[PDB]
Image (tube, coloured by chain):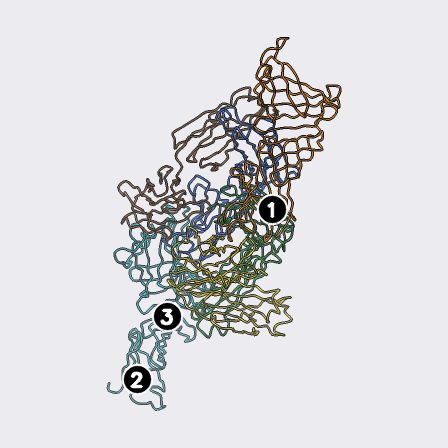
Chain colours: A brown, B yellow, C green, D blue, E cyan, F orange
Amino acid sequence: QIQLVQSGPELKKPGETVKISCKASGYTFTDYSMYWVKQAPGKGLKRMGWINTETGEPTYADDFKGRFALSLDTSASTAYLHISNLKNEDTATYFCARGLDSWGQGTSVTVSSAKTTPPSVYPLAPGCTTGSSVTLGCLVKGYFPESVTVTWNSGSLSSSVHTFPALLQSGLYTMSSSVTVPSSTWPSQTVTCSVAHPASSTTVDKKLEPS
Amino acid sequence: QIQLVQSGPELKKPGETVKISCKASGYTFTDYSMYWVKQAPGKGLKRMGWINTETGEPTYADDFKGRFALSLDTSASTAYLHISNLKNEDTATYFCARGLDSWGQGTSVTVSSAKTTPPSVYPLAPGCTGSSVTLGCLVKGYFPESVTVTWNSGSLSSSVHTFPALLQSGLYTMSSSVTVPSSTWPSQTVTCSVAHPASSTTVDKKLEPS
Amino acid sequence: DIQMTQSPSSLSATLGGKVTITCKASQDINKYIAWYQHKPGKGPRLLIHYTSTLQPGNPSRFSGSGSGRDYSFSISNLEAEDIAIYYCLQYDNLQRTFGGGTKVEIKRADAAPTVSIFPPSSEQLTSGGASVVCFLNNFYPKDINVKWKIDGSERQNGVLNSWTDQDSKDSTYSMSSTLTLTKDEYERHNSYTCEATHKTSTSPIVKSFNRNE
Amino acid sequence: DIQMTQSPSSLSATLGGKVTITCKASQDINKYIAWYQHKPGKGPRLLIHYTSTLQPGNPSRFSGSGSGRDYSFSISNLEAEDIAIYYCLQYDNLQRTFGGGTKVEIKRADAAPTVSIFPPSSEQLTSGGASVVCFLNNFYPKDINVKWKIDGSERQNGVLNSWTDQDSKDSTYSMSSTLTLTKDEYERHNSYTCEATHKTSTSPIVKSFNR
Amino acid sequence: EKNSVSVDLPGEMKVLVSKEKNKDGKYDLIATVDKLELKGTSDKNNGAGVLEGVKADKSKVKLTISDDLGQTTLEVFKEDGKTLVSKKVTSKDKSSTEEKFNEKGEVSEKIITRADGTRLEYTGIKSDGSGKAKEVLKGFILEGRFTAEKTTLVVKEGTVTLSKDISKSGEVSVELQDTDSSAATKKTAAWNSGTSTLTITVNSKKTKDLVFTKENTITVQQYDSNGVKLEGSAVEITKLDEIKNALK
Amino acid sequence: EKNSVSVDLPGEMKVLVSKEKNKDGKYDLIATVDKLELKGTSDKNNGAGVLEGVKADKSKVKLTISDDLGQTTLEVFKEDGKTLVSKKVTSKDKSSTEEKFNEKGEVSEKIITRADGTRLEYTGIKSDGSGKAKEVLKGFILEGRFTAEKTTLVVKEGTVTLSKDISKSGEVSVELQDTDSSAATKKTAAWNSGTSTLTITVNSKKTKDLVFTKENTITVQQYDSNGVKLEGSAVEITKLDEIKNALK
């Protein structure tokens, strides 16, 4: 029905410019102002500004001056957020909103001098005693930017899975993922972790070998 | 002892300048950098900058370039914070700090176009009785913020509530409660002494029965 | 600058309990964390430095632990006078940075408000104003609703509701509700009521007066 | 802009109970307040509008009250899936502003961690690095201390400790602890230990292996 | 007659006052109300006084004129001359209160006519001072109820209710309710007491301003597409169904 | 004689190798140590072979020379010829290990001499692989302890304890501890393993860098007044008192 659908996650270097799109459906676009909101770590939700969808006239908040531009393609029911001279402070999730009941899904922007880097994936198998269950895992190391997906046996294993938030070390991300399964499953059968890294268009798979 | 003592509260209009002092005693001033920290309601503590007390070289946090300057009178063991082009966002408490163990008491800065205004002080007495009787003073239409309601010269403080001020049409209104045994009033006299330093006013109001 | 992520942002605990606050740094800070207590109208006070050293002048109910990036601070045997905002500070770098703070509140047994209503004074009335005031004293929890009725009709605008800070002794809250009118508005009506709805009852405590006297 | 003061900024409550968040405006806002639920990586979700109205698609466990400047929002019959950051929003003015937000957490019974130790994989060693990992799974409360020892001596720096957010199913937390070495360093020592200090026990849970 | 001077009165009535004091010292007075001539005496010569008489149905009629000529009171009693049937008090501004009485002489109906011709009709009066109310405006009628404290007129459209309050003192306030739970469609509004305006908003967006004027009229003005600013000019509501229109 | 070709050895000593094969087909070797004459025969003709002698006190001396001529192993046995008293291994790079042995073939004491002349002396050794340790540097001596895992040398000054760890692999790390509770005076420090530097701070302020060099020296350098930058030049610690004064 009524949707705000935003553009995908963005990686830029400091100094650069970024453009986030917000595509509306299911109502007359010019009947609501479009609001833009910044989600920053620990800084809740903040109004950046809004734009009159009929006139194109933008009104920015004080903290969003100079390097911020709100624009429109009314015929395409699309609003745009353009941020220039990107700084580390601009690393955040950006949202479009109209009325009280419509929100975009968020667009995450990373400003960083790091280059895109695929993950190495290493198995965590118990070193050479087994109990009634076995906890296994994968270490996803040395990737950038931060977004990855760790999937166990193609989703067969989802219930006893823990996804550990990534941290920076040596300018690159490390995350890990755990699964616990009965001694009857492994190493009797097979458990494999599958790791995707959208920014590098990569998927990589690792089988948990015993002993 | 070691003390950092900061200069008193300030009210300024937009576009004006303020200069806050921090006087250090009890130690060799040049042995420690001085830190300045901003505290606004809605933020915690954010480092604005620090200054090398020996060289005079300041280092500013990212958000505090342009309008803010740190300086020194080393012989007087006094460090100064300057802010030009004052804006509403500069309404805050500002603190100086040295080492891990020394803080100033804070300097309240209010930037506003409103003018200093003495409170009107009204009595809150019961209209025409159990064990205790609650009375109050309504303190209305004043600016800037700080007022101290003193009840019976501090004799009654155990049972006092100071209700924080709220802005309404550009001026503050605050209130104060006190509860006494029903036997002591109106038998004995209770008075509120409202001090508003910025307007040089102290108004005493005696709470009469009705 | 190093980010210091302090958790939780707010704590509520019963007297005699142990509360713990954490602070996670964006890199190793080599045990160079200190913890401060900040009370209204004062400089912050150092409690803990170098992760776990208790600063003289403070009880050994305050503690700290940690290494690398991860640190914690505890108050054991929590007392009513421990109400404060607490902050972590990293000083590994010259560019010292703070955690976001933890507001520590006391959880106590529920208490109903003592409510008092006050008509405008003669002196206020002389001067064109008319403020009606209700005091709601010594209640818990903090959440409360006051609704003003004039001649039985809700008046939603022009109400000044101000809560005290949590009481450093008895851990209650008190609140003042002020409806300010003009003299002329005040003299258009007879009945003035403040209704207080609190978790201590499904029915509101109601206080009321008539200008009819 | 109208300031919205949201309290408390965080709360921890047992399931089935009732929690209440307040929001104080800097002026009268004419009952134009709405409340949103925000889970990580999903867009904000409207629960209440016009102070007390329940938006369709949501349980009547969500409610709101107030007028003038003073408002509240409540969750009755607290569920484990209600974990989120909740925000008030005033829309009396074109310059809409948000409260600072409330993290809602579940208070539950204390749980000890299951701790598992993993030596570096063959493949990681063959590349020349050596990461040691301990999983601390399904504990409560969240606060936990991990101590690494090499040949019995503490190693404090270079450790990556990542906590999950609260499980929406058992209200527990898990933590991964990763110590990154070179192969060279790893092969200079024999004993590797991870010590887990949790309030559940006065004695650490210790996991140790010898290369 | 060159012997009695007509002075015009509130309600456009005219009373002749004798030039000369009668044999007992009191000026004799004559008026013809609803073609029924009435006579009386007063020690005043300005017009002020009581005039009485009977109608075709033996009904006793009495026209008390204010000392200052500022007000006429027409009272209708039964043939007895005692039991009151009706009373109309008409001011020089053309404002008029008309009351019918019952067995005890308690008020059974009341009509307040404002100077401008708009009226409030109170009927169906319970004995606590609640009952049925109607407001006659220029172009249309509003229907509702009343209490001792306020008169409330109500206009409904779909799930939306507009309630217009008139206090004892005469103060107007207006409220809107809507039981609709969807933010997309719920009508909500705020009342500005200073400009006597109800602003309706839907899904955060201002849609229209209804102004309740001192002329006892209602104007409507639309906001632009985005609800930033009023467009065009306000228009006075000539018909009830136009109010309802504005609640969709 | 020139019947033998002589060759200098690790330590300071020359072994003569019979230029030709002896009467029994092998190479005869003679060396001079502790004014003793040692003799042996070997299949090798570079100086690699075992020599023996007996002392005046009927100690057996045995000089095993490595194939590479890079290491001498000199053993002292008592009269039996089996029970070992001491063993020194000396490499050509000026390095060494001397051990004094006890009954049951147990080491009672051990001296590691590094190439540079600095030494590590292990004494009062126990079954748990623990005991007393001492580090002899150029100018001063450090005293501490050892375990199977690491040697710890310790310098104390007031409430301050400085611990210098040497892992079994030879890795150096340093810790500072101070029981002082006051921020104003508590000595604290962080160890940079990359630069082998312990940076001391007091009350958030850097005071000095102690650098533990690969040449087994310790240097000190003070920071400026505000602890923003190192001042002057690093200075070598010549004496123990200097280390202690750095902890005050």
Chain bearing tag 3 is: E
Pick the residue in front: E134 or B124.
B124
For residue E97, the mark is 3
Say yes or no: labels 2 and 1 on the same chain: no
Q: Quadrant of residue D13?
A: top right
Seen at 38% across and 43% down, the residue is: A95
Q: Amino acid at mark 3?
A: Thr
Residue at 33% of width from left, 61% of height from top? E212
Q: Which residue is mark 2?
A: E17
* Residue at the outermost top position: F24
- Helix, strand or loop under label 1: helix
Tell me whether marks 2 and 3 sit on the same chain: yes
Mark carried by residue C143: none
User: In the displayed structure, would residue B106 be above or below residue D148?
Assistant: below
- Please state if F197 lies on the left or on the right of E15 as rendered: right
Q: Residue furthest left?
A: E2
Amino acid on which disc 2 is placed: Val
* x and y, in percent, of residue C23 in the image: 54, 45
Question: At label 1, which amino acid type do we have?
Answer: Glu
Q: Secondary structure at mark 2?
A: strand
Q: Nearer the viewer, residue D147 or C189?
A: D147
Q: CA distance from mark 2 to mark 1?
A: 128 Å
Mark pair 2, 3: CA separation? 26 Å
Residue under pointer 1: F242
- Near mark 3 (Cα within 10 A), the count class, few <14, some 14-19 or many ≥20, is some
Whole-percent x, y for residue A131 in the image: 62, 25
Task: Tell me which numbered mark, 2 or 3, is placed earlier along the sequence.
Answer: 2
Q: Nearer the viewer, residue E176 or F130?
A: F130
Identify whether C144 is placed above or below D57: below
Tell me how far mark 1 sits from mark 3, CA to CA.
109 Å
